[PDB]
Length: 186
Ligand SMILES: Cc1cccc(CC(=O)Nc2cccnc2)c1
Image (cartoon, rainbow, N blue to C red; front, side):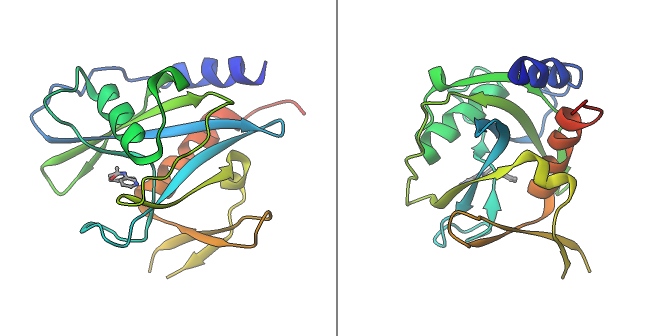
């Protein structure tokens, strides 16, 4: 099946806990895969305009590890619940992708999660201004604007709203799309 095929592909790229004990300032992100209308989508947030870091930017759910977290995956799931109301029974964490090093002292660990079809986002407005889906296939043929660095513009055909997706968030989206969608019979 589509979902079994995605999980099988993803597992081949799982680094697991290899980098998890290293003494960094630690953050995790959840790359949430949603199946709608027979296709996979990624779920993104738009960060509230009131956050100090990166107000109004498109981001995956996630945040800083805290002492309660059993592991880095727990961080991602805790933060996703806080930001968009995703409950743990509503997500299957399939793998841990390559971590992202930033600022010389920070390591961001991305986890891919399969999201239950009955999940409906409840954006927490103190953290998230919007939640939206993008089809995973978009990231194979994105609409690129050069601001010099590359920015994706995605327009939701449901409402005509355009989102800008940049940086680590854009990079990770492409990676997930390659992993899951490369070399597939039609
Ligand atoms: C791509 C990336 C880079 C750095 C940190 C994060 C996690 C995060 O802060 N997510 C978040 C927070 C609040 C609202 N929406 C999303 C993600």
